[PDB]
Image 1 (cartoon, each protein chain N blue to C red):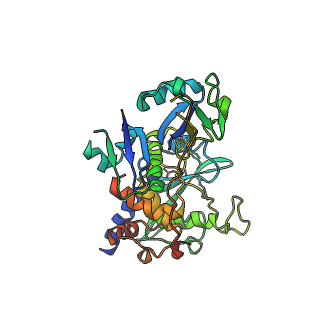
Image 2 (cartoon, helix red, strand yellow):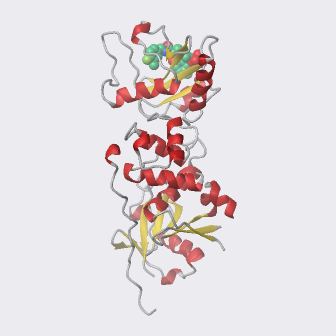
Image 3 (cartoon, rainbow over the protein chains, first blue to last red):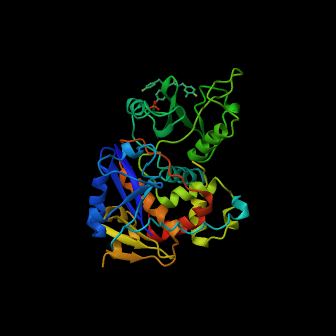
Length: 100
Length: 169
Length: 86
Ligand SMILES: Cc1cc(CNC(=O)[C@H](Cc2ccc(OP(=O)(O)O)cc2)NC(=O)Cc2ccc(F)cc2)ccc1F
């Protein structure tokens, strides 16, 4: 049922239903980001998604995207759509040798 | 006294575990543990006049219950299952737990019962009442890495928080 | 309803305002944005992950799973969790 994700752009925390459509996701980004769904594109892994399918039909499960380990998703916003660019987070420093 | 102080200290860390269930019944325990994987455990108050706390743990046969004994400032598993010399004593009931948990983690004990009579307690992961503090979820994580917290690149105040709960479960 | 949280390397995070109020230090301060200038991004992302893990599993109805914390960021995120009071 519930499936917890992370929309990341150049990151949004949210939960969704396994039966929710991919178009239903573009409506949630419209609320906060204030951009129309027609000006939106999603990219699970490196693959675009049809707005008619659901999250499960695109490979999202409550076992894969738990709240403690949420599977993340990407977004690409003039004339043409932009490219999907997501910047990783900082690198955790080296382990102190005692904790190694 | 030394007993009275160490006693209240034992319950105070028991409140920090997040897997202490206070006033709970066996039937409430049997239900909350009916679906958990083998090895899941919890600690609750005991319904016997001579016992305070009791371990409720899931096995392949279903949930079962073991009582914890207190005698002259020492915690140990119920002495009616084995000779007392084979039942290690402790100060904090949490240290008792962490010891029997870490033994199974070290594969010094398995889910099958020994045939030479010694105590057999299979414990894996605890069952939490509520999601603990993120702070506490590192105190656990850090303790699974090292027991020399005072040799860490930490502020002294943070280390004193670690020293209050030194266990790995 | 939503809040934006900024890290040291500038990474922006948008979570439910209820998810952010589990942290006590954030609750006192509530524009609808907060800049954390000591907490790097790799730590800032996990605290929000703890926020969901806290809201979803405040009830014991569902079996609470363990929160996975890698030992490398444990030192840092303990200091951050003490900052945010969560
Ligand atoms: C793990 C382990 C177990 C044993 C022997 N254990 C028992 O035979 C206990 C006795 C007991 C009963 C209540 C109790 O709770 P309380 O009295 O409130 O403390 C404490 C102990 N019987 C049961 O479990 C049967 C049962 C099961 C589910 C229920 F829903 C109700 C009852 C020896 C070694 C060992 F390694």
